[PDB]
Every structure is written in structure tokens, then in C-alpha cells.
Amino acid sequence: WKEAKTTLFCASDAKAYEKEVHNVWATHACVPTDPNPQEMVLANVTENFNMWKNDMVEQMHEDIISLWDESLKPCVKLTGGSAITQACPKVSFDPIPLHYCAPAGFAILKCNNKTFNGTGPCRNVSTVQCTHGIKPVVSTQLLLNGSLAEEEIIIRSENLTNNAKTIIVHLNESVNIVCTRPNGSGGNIRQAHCNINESKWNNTLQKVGEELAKHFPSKTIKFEPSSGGDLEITTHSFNCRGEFFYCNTSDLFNGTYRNGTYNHTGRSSNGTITLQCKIKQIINMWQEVGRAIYAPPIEGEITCNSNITGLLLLRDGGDTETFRPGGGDMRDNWRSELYKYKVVEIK
Amino acid sequence: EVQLVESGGGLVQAGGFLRLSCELRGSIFNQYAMAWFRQAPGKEREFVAGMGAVPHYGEFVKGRFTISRDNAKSTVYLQMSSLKPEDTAIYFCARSKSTYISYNSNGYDYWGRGTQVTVSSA
Ligand SMILES: *[C@@H]1O[C@H](CO)[C@@H](O)[C@H](O)[C@H]1NC(C)=O
Ligand SMILES: *[C@@H]1O[C@H](CO)[C@@H](O)[C@H](O)[C@H]1NC(C)=O
Ligand SMILES: *[C@@H]1O[C@H](CO)[C@@H](O)[C@H](O)[C@H]1NC(C)=O
Ligand SMILES: *[C@@H]1O[C@H](CO)[C@@H](O)[C@H](O)[C@H]1NC(C)=O
Ligand SMILES: *[C@@H]1O[C@H](CO)[C@@H](O)[C@H](O)[C@H]1NC(C)=O
Ligand SMILES: *[C@@H]1O[C@H](CO)[C@@H](O)[C@H](O)[C@H]1NC(C)=O
Ligand SMILES: *[C@@H]1O[C@H](CO)[C@@H](O)[C@H](O)[C@H]1NC(C)=O
Image (cartoon, each protein chain N blue to C red):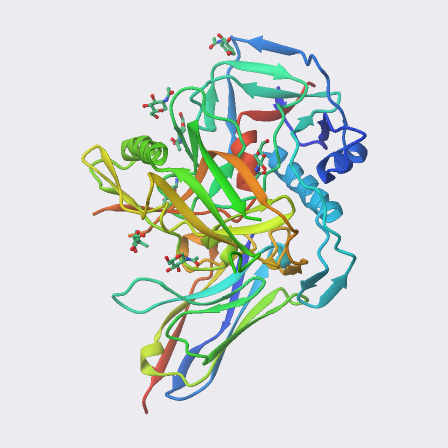
């Protein structure tokens, strides 16, 4: 069981007849997935994992960059010294699950410890040929459409003492988020909004605040909106149906957790938290430094009904502790699903 | 292994011009945004100027500073004009964790050693 790097390959259940661009890309870039993949539990062996130094993440990153290069073609791409022009037709866009697979001579160890924080020893290890299916959802602040924690909320970080290390909050219950650009009674084709059930979110940060306090005891735990910067990271940004949404989260990350109780202080209405969103055409790229420019949005109603399954938090540096939404490095998005896996060489 | 080579700075007369530069080594430049923070004595490190896809400036800048990227030289530059005693501080180069700029110092995992800028009024 000697840890090792090697070129993984992706597998998917992509469908030959599907025009959706994830299917199209996986059709030529991945192999079909197995209906019954074998898994061999080993209750005896204990191996150490490290989700923050896992070469599987970097290989996934390169594939997703590569998928976006073939799929979401911008009208023009501006990178410092250059400007590339292409046809930018509108496209059908809906992420599908990708599995990562070890070539022969290597195996994938899977941690079965349902509260494993991503670092150190895992006592219950399995062997699989491929990971489970991971939807490559590119987003900031909120992790969408992932998998849930099995027991309690899990706090992951490379080092909770180092405030510059991103914190990944793995929820154990999804929180529904519905964003829509609706179909003069209309006035702007670039305005959208998201709805989140207030009590569901009140209960979430209550239990997230409980887990955070375990790590930062005797402190008031505050949630505050993003620090300033690029719009991609100061808002909850994500792609919906090919359109780039930027959703303001100031009413979302806005509460205090004192004396074991969470007190939401963001704005709310019919028991619902609303985020105002813009659809933007000029976006700052996450694949590399520069800008990409897209056509105006499609007609009709644009809706993404998603499941928040995790959060990206950052703690302010210095008698209190303040947490803001983070993200930006999509490697953390892949880490949040690949944490339990580790590629190993069967010498 | 990542290192930031800082250049420029030191003593300026009030109203003068100064240039700061910072070469990123052991990392792919066009993968990371770069920024300058400053720390005056007794104060919190504060964001000055940063650039990934687009430049950002701290509120106290007021169009006096220009930040730019040189991909060929893996270097980012800060041109500071109309400097004032208020601008005296240790200036730190920083490499972002990503392609994006945050104003909060915790969006950065690599920091230069810091160079003193002192603005003297004769
Ligand atoms: C290991 O994980 C599997 C997966 O659910 C579980 O069925 C089994 O009981 C676990 N074994 C140990 C020793 O924890
Ligand atoms: C989720 O975790 C919290 C604490 O992290 C716990 O109080 C709650 O019961 C869990 N939800 C379940 C097990 O459905
Ligand atoms: C995860 O657990 C390991 C060992 O059990 C510990 O060293 C590490 O600090 C933990 N990390 C977090 C974020 O709790
Ligand atoms: C965690 O962060 C602190 C402060 O940033 C640092 O001093 C410490 O060495 C880090 N822990 C480890 C295990 O590297
Ligand atoms: C979000 O909305 C508030 C107004 O309610 C505004 O002050 C804040 O700057 C907005 N944030 C961003 C990143 O646009
Ligand atoms: C929290 O929400 C209220 C109402 O939306 C807002 O006025 C306040 O500024 C927010 N807190 C922040 C942005 O820190
Ligand atoms: C999340 O998944 C649902 C159902 O699979 C889909 O309708 C929605 O568009 C997805 N959201 C994102 C941001 O991909």
C-alpha cells in the first residue's frame, strides 16, 4: 500500500444521444462506468489520508478545465497579452457524475469512517476501482449538488489555527436553493433571485455554529458577508443552464451564534431568504487569470433548483470569531467530494 | 517551492513617486492573482492594490497607484505617485490562493518579507 501518483482516468454514464455538453465531453473523454463495481472492505488495515495534498484533486481540476474549454466557449477570451475569438452559441448545460478510476497496478482506497475529517488515520478502509459519481459543479461560497455527511456536520480544514486555510463545512442535511431568472411588467433579462427556506437555514447555521464552537470554544461565533474583491468570490456564483449567475449573499451569511443559540440577522420575508442575482456576460475566469465574454442570456425562464450540501468559510484574523463565505479555488470543490479517496500502488 | 522576490520601496519625499515590483517564482503566474497589502505600526494589515483579471484598489488610493501584471516576467508592479506621510508602512507582496482577488488577507497563502516605504516631508 505505497502511496503514489499516476494518471487516473474518468468514467461516466454519459449517454450517446445527449446533446448536453457534459455528456458530449464525457463520451469522448471518459469510458463507460460499471453497473456493479466491486468494493472490498478491509476492517483490519488503517491508512492515513490527506484531502489537502491529494493528487486526485489536481487531475480532476485539469479534466474540468478541459471540459469547460470544449463546452462553454466564450465569444472572446482576454488573457493579458492575447484575445481569442470563437463562435459562442448557446448550449445545453447540466453537470453529470464523473467517476475517477485507478489504472491497473494501482487501487483507490476509500475511507469508510463516516465522521472522517479528511486528515490522519482512518480505521475502516475499503478498496474500489472507481470513486463514486461526482458532479463537477463550479461555484463559490455554497457547495451545490454534492453528497451529504452521513452522521453529524463535519468541519474540514488543513489547519483550523491558520485562518488563511479554507474551511469546508460538510452538511448532513441538504438545504434547498431555487434560483430563477423569470420569463413594463418585465424590465431586465439579467435579474434573477434565489429563495432559501429561512427556518431550514436558521437550523443549519445553528448546527454549523455548534460544530464551529467545539473548535473555537468560549467565543461568540459570527457569520458575516464576504470581504470585498472579485465579484465571483464576493457573491455566490455558479453556472445555471449555461448562464453565469452572481447571487448576493449578504442576507444569508449574517447571524450570530451566542450561548448555544443561533440568531439570524439577515433580512427575510415570508419565512424566506431572498438573494438578488445578476446574470453577467464579462466573467473573471477560474481556469486561469483573465476574462471571458459571453452572449446575453437565453429567452424564457431559467431555473436551477439545487441542494446546498456544503459551505466554504474563512475565519477573520485577529475576543470573538467571525466567519465569511469563501471559495474561488475550485480544487476545494473537488476536495469536498474526493476527501475520502486516495490512490495507492499495489506493488 | 514558492517564493516572492520583492523590489523597490524605501524612502520617498512627500509628493514623490515610487515603484514596487514582485516576482513570483516556483509557481505558475497566470494561475494566481497578486496583491499588495500594507501594515502601518499599530494597525491591521490592509489591502492596497491587487490584480487577477482586473485591478482593485483600496479606498485610500484615489487613483494615485497603478497595478499591472507582466506574464513574461512573472511579475506584478505597483506604481505609486503623490505619496503622503499617511502612506508610510511596510508593504507586503502576496500571492492569492486562486485566480481571484480578496481584500481580506486570508485569501492569500504566500507573502513577501515586506519592504518599508517611508514618506518624508523634508
Ligand atoms: C466499514 O464501513 C462499512 C460501510 O458502511 C460498514 O458496513 C462496516 O461496518 C464498517 N466497518 C468498520 C469496522 O467500521
Ligand atoms: C447533523 O449534525 C448535527 C451536529 O453536527 C446533529 O445535531 C444533527 O442531529 C445531525 N443531523 C442528523 C443526524 O440527521
Ligand atoms: C482531523 O483529525 C486529525 C487526527 O484525528 C487531527 O490531527 C486534525 O487536526 C483534525 N482536523 C480537523 C479540522 O479537525
Ligand atoms: C497551523 O497554523 C499555525 C498558525 O498559522 C502554525 O503555527 C502551525 O504550525 C500550523 N500547524 C501545523 C501542524 O503546521
Ligand atoms: C449585496 O447587497 C447589498 C445591498 O443590500 C450591498 O450593500 C452589497 O455591497 C452587495 N454585495 C455585493 C458583493 O454586491
Ligand atoms: C445583515 O442584514 C441586514 C438587513 O438585510 C443589513 O442591514 C445588515 O447590514 C447586514 N449585516 C452585514 C451586511 O454585516
Ligand atoms: C443541481 O442538480 C439539479 C438536479 O440534478 C439540477 O436541476 C440543478 O440545475 C443543479 N444545479 C447546478 C448549479 O448545477
